[PDB]
Length: 142
Ligand SMILES: [Mg+2]
Image (cartoon, rainbow, N blue to C red; front, side):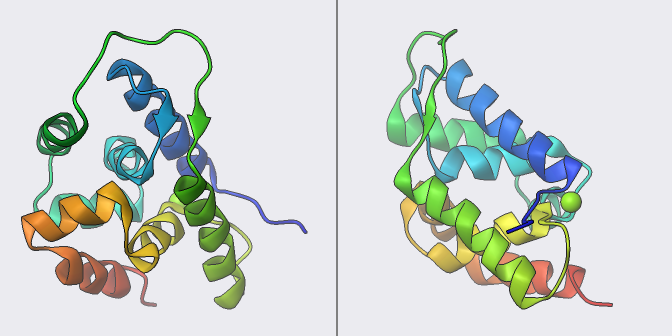
């Protein structure tokens, strides 16, 4: 009942929304959360994604290839059910690990665990789904 995101995780989610808006997408999907995690730069998830080889430009391009893009949106937009499930799962992972704060690493763990959705399609297309998981797992050791 006291589940809470770290500041970096909150920033990543804000960036996910900002990315969707930029692309004229009114629904924030797993792909936007993934791009938000990369754009956040500082957290484990960004360091994992960059280590396995993604750039912001690549992810954005793939999102556009798959979904298209429309004019920028200025009003409020919303999380898809899968995005909501991913965020709920990130809390579940943090509680399983008995950690107080849901970080970027927990959100990326949850994206991978969820297994479906555009973010996983992009990881799979790039051939780095299991490599991303491995890198995330070692980056969470200590
Ligand atoms: Mg964090």
